Amino acid sequence: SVATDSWSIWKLQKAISVLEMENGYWWCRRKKQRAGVMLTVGTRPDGSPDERWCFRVGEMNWATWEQTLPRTLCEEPSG
Amino acid sequence: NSALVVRMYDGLLQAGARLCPNVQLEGIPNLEGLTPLKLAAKEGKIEIFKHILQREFSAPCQSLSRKFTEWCYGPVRVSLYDLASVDSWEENSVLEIIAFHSRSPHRHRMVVLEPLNKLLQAKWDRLIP
Amino acid sequence: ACIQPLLEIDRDSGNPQPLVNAQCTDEYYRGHSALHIAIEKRSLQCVKLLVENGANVHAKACGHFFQKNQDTCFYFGELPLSLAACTKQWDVVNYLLENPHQPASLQAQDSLGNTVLHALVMIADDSAENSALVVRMYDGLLQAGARLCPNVQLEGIPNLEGLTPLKLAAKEGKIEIFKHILQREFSAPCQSLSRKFTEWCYGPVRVSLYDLASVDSWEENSVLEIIAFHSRSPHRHRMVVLEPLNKLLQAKWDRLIPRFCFNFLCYLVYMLIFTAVAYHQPALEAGNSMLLLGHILILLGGVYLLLGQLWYFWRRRLFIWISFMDSYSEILFLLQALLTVLSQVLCFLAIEWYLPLLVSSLVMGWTNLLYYTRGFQHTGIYSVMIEKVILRDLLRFLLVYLVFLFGFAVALVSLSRPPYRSILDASLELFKFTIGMGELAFQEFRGVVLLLLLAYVLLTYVLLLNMLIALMSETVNSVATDSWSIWKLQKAISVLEMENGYWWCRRKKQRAGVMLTVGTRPDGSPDERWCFRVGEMNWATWEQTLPRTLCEEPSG
Amino acid sequence: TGIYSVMIEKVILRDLLRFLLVYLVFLFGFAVALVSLSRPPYRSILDASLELFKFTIGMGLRFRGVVLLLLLAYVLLTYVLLLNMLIALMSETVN
Ligand SMILES: C=C(C)[C@]12C[C@@H](C)[C@@]34O[C@](Cc5ccccc5)(O[C@@H]1[C@@H]3C=C(COC(=O)Cc1ccc(O)c(OC)c1)C[C@]1(O)C(=O)C(C)=C[C@@H]41)O2
Ligand SMILES: [Ca+2]
Ligand SMILES: [Ca+2]
């Protein structure tokens, strides 16, 4: 057996719990709220602006210097 | 197999942006009402499921990407992950599919993926009380 | 194209406070300057231009974003030079060091008192790509520093925490560079910068010298003292085994075997007196004065142990607070001393509760004797695994087992036998069965009792297998080298405490290294160093080239 | 059968002797603490430690509370040593 599996199987157990908690026992309709923040990622193929509900994940990569820089939304670190 | 699938799949999305811009190909459901991503989730196709969630495209046709970078300073950066088909808020979400609908032995492997694992950690922290 | 015109306008507008040096103001981005931006954008041509128009090459970006403790924040030192260095832009670094108008200074330090070396120690992590970068830049700056400022020893500059780059690497658990610094050799002219030399070399054999400056216990806040007590990294034990330190710590131990055995005898004796005192206790009712003699010693020794442990925690443990995981052995001695002194007070004050406290201190005192097993390797590893198993692993098994025990205990007594249940007597009677002590007693629904019992015995067995499997899985997954290091660090703790001294102080013990004139041509008088000599034997040396040596022969 | 006898010798010497050293210290220390509690016709620390050993085998008011609590910790620690000894064997065989 893969050593990582037991840990992932647990994270899935939590995933089951979290989703059912959001449903609710008898007061079911309360835990209905979107996650993440909605931002304008860019323009679509269809002229309208491409807006999306996004989740923020911080990253640090030390080998990126050689590769090209990605197009970014903001000009400087914010928040 | 996986290397072909991601390479072919992406090449078709780019072509679709040029040949049929108004059409969102990943929005077309099948008779079972599953989009390609939800299908990958239900059928336990990890490698492409992973690739779709964290997709990056440069210069033209930038829009068809599920991962973006808000800002970047030196090594640090903040990445944005599209949650459209992902968020539990929506009906028949990817998470709900994996949690309950999928019948692959490796569902647990699927939960631990960059956008989903962080998201589930966030929701858990909110639900401790 | 607008920057050069734009700045000329600003100057021609009579701005007293030039625009180029304008800096950000919010607590988040405080201090950032246009030069910082040009460096981060990796544009030397822009860097040159900003400097050529009076850009302050020593402006500090001190805001929250540029701080070491924050999450999703980049700490690179605060200065432009540290930025360029920390983002691997030698083309920028060289210009900041070599431009004629305004050379950047290698001595400059930030709000934390950190130089470019300090920062490079901070940004480094154990990933391979990062580590290779840091050493390359770190060394490349030392060579430059030898050229730009010979008289200054850059690694000698401490920060506000009084830590040099090496000590910083030690406290922050930066192995790859810490290891590199200790085993550093230079082949270029600046031979003085290297900390490793070869005294002499004969055939396959040779002796290598390791600089002990920041390492040796003689100086305050030594690397060894820092790692043992100040560092708070999980892989600190990994650092102790590095080539120069392991040999060095073994040397210090070998000289300290007597003191260890002596202290073992003392504690053993103290326990024997403690043993006799508790055995001869008669509860309600020269010789009787001698029994008081015993109690006196116990009180005297218990405070001394309590004082000693307090001194250990008093000396360096004030900012640690809960160091239970780090020093499991140290805690028990304090509790034993604490419990022993408290027991004597009650004994003097005729309190009937002292006896439990007295015996409790006795039993614990003898068990604590396992402390001294660290002298030998085999027993030392066994004692380490005891500590590990008891500490982290037993809590979870027991917590689960009680739930099974309690739940099954209530159900079986409630089922068997107006009927008087004792949760204690119940759980006790069921625990002793598994423990093998006693046997279950029939009340005289027997059928249900048997089925329930079957579930218990098997399920209890399942828990054992999980504990074995979970315990077993840790050993296979754990690196074979890892378990041994934890012991060598325990020894490192002992040697350092012995060098501290008792209450009748035995300080300023003899230095462990030998001082030699490693460098012939420093800028000035010859440079002397306290080095540790380590013998080496290499049978594949014939193909490789011979190293430059201090001596010509093993003699001298 | 001959290799089986080789492993017995190895296990007895390197692993069991080490357990025995730790186990005896625990046995002595806990036996004396239990005797000091008993306190009169005094059972010898030997006679006591014997009584505590046969207790483990299952053969068979400060006094009541401490006596029981101390014993419960004893049974656990003795089992810990066995589990540790078993773990020590597994790590030795792989190497
Ligand atoms: C608070 C702690 C850390 C602690 C105190 C007591 C209860 C302890 O059991 C533990 C856990 C325990 C409690 C109750 C039942 C089983 C286990 O571990 C130690 C503590 C652990 C033991 C077992 O011996 C050891 O700790 C090994 C050891 C001793 C000294 C060392 O310097 C050492 O470092 C390597 C290791 C001795 C006891 O203190 C003891 O003699 C009594 C009566 C119980 C043991 O609790
Ligand atoms: Ca049995
Ligand atoms: Ca067994």
Image (cartoon, coloured by chain):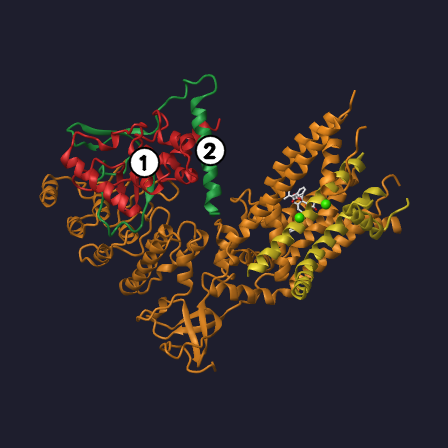
Chain colours: A green, B red, C orange, D yellow
| Residue C301 in view | no
How far is disc 2 from disc 1 in space, using C-alphas? 38 Å
Q: Position of residue C227 (x, y in %)?
A: 49, 54
Which residue position is annotated with label 2?
Answer: A14
For badge 2, the amino acid type reads Lys
Between residues A74 and C48, which one lies in front from this camera angle? Answer: A74
Instruction: Determine the image quadrant of residue C490.
Output: bottom right
Describe the element under mark 1 as helix, strand or loop: loop
Which mark's residue is nearer the viewer, 2 or 1?
2
Q: Residues within 10 Å of mark 1 (few under 14, many from 20)?
A: few
Chain assignment, label 1: C
Where residue C300 sits in the image (x, y, percent)? Answer: 73, 49
Q: Residue C6: x, y in percent?
A: 11, 41
Query: Is residue C412 shown above or below C284?
Result: above
- Determine crowd level at label 2: few under 14, some 14-19, many 20+ residues with C-alpha closer than 10 A: some
Q: Amino acid at mark 1?
A: Glu
Tell me, for residue C310, which label it has, or none. Answer: none
Report the residue at 35% width, 46% height from top: C111
Q: At x 88% / y 51%, what residue is drawn?
A: C287
Q: Name the residue that disc number 1 marks.
A: C27
From where the camera sits, is residue B86 visible? yes
Q: Is residue C445 above or below residue D29?
A: above
Q: Residue at x 39, y 65 (%)?
A: C184
Mark 2, ligand 1, within 8 Å: the answer is no
Subunit of mark 2? A
Q: Quadrant of residue B30?
A: top left
Judge left or right: residue D62 versus residue C399: right
| Residue drawn 58% across the image and 60% down it | D93
